[PDB]
Image (cartoon, rainbow, N blue to C red; front, top):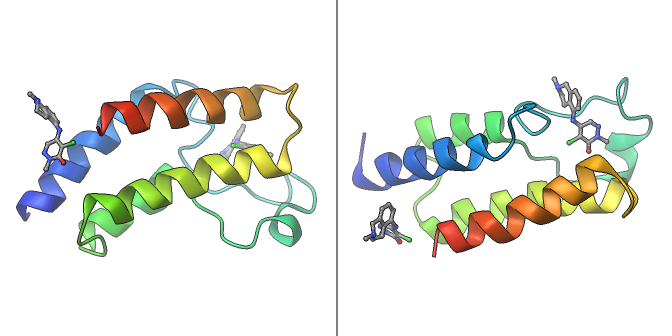
Length: 101
Ligand SMILES: CN1CCc2c(cccc2Nc2cnn(C)c(=O)c2Cl)C1
Ligand SMILES: CN1CCc2c(cccc2Nc2cnn(C)c(=O)c2Cl)C1
């Protein structure tokens, strides 16, 4: 594991601690979220992010942060402002970015 891989594994562990229900742990299915794949062009989740780290698909912290933001943006797009996923996505976006400086 390269230095970037190690740093990103650290960040991912800390980010996932902010999602204790694991709402962002795995891809959203259309079964749980009707029409999701039609509304969200580029899905993302922490599990996919983990696989990308292990496959050495991130070459910068900027790339990793963009996937994190994509995941949060997707939750803020499909879900309405009032809602649990929207609020958590917005919360962890800000805290996570701060955490990753
Ligand atoms: C395997 N996981 C997939 C994701 C998930 C599960 C359970 C409860 C909430 C979620 N996460 C959702 C679900 N629906 N929507 C619309 C979302 O935006 C998220 Cl993050 C089961
Ligand atoms: C004193 N701080 C320095 C920063 C830091 C610490 C611990 C865990 C992650 C970080 N943050 C990093 C580390 N390395 N790189 C390359 C970064 O870009 C960031 Cl934000 C301890």
